[PDB]
Length: 79
Length: 414
Image (tube, rainbow over all chains, first blue to last red; front, side, top):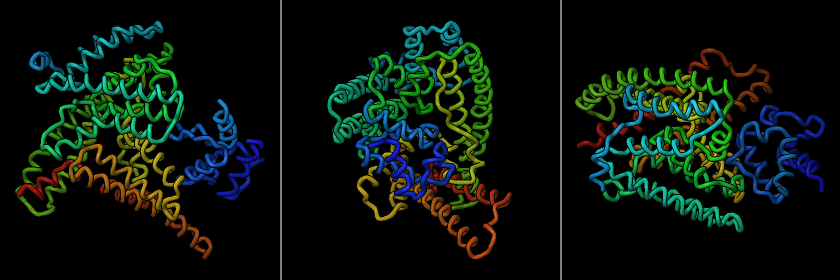
């Protein structure tokens, strides 16, 4: 299955808002993710993709937009 | 051999203005070198070892051996994990290596509870060095670190300007900064910032921290003691005076640390960002002892929240957030020391942050309660903002009174 399609479909499962077309939005500023909401996404991103996500290297400008989340998951999936 | 180290000359780091004459002359080749994109690897360690040794050659100069033990002990368990992490990756192995890297620090803290005296493993920068050491175990665990020299590990862990108390650093960021020497005018920019930071540090440490710490604080304590009771007006005096003293002494130090680091080419993380104008307890920890807070945020808090959400241990979203806060700030208290008031100082900011967070949640639902019932949003203006600042400032200042351990003198001297 497609990496981009599953990230798009996990985001509106826990938070309930599709952001497929308007995708380069800052998810913190757009009101999608809480302080606690990011932790909830990380857990489900691990359960779905079988990848363990580095949160102690997680910068603020690193994994903020959905495109940087999609592209970051693929890099951690093989490389 | 111990008597030799005690005979050896001693210079307390940033102890006086005339200290910077030595360090200035000493670092001058390093700085000039960086303009031609070269480092003097051998000379950098020599000048580092000299100043670290001079910082440790006190009346308890024997601690140099405790440092020597520490470097050996850390090399063993850092490399032990490095070797292991290549092939396998297990939870408990990582936990064991984490425990073992922090064990000397645990022994130093725990000791005077049992003994009433210090640990033999104790040396000056131990509390701040340990963060650099565990940092690598955590970074190897996350698979973000793979390659490193013994030289790269040693340069980072026992970096000279940030040794004794200086800003906490992470390996990946320190290493990359050291790896690529900044270009000619960016380097001159750092000289400008270094000469600025020294000027401020002079004012902060030798002028202001002097007035609060050595001038106002001692008679205020003396009076508060004579007054008696669980609180008095001179005790309200020590609360503010010490608070400012703590800030000015530590912030001034931090500026010196950053300035020397700059002359050494790398730019260490900053510690303070106008902490007293913070409206929020949440905002305060983004402004106070930042290198420590930002470490504890990513390495203790963030990591703990995932575990409580992996295992879904608590009922709702907010209890896992609350428990993480109280544990995280309490561990930070234990880090300061295993005495009642450091632990108190911990639990304080713990319940302080949960109260703070609960309010932000309540304010958003009161605003929705108003908007749907017709009414305009709850007022947010210059006086609500100031009120916030006022409440925060005094919560913060009261915590520093607990932290000072003066309440031990006032309540428990007997």
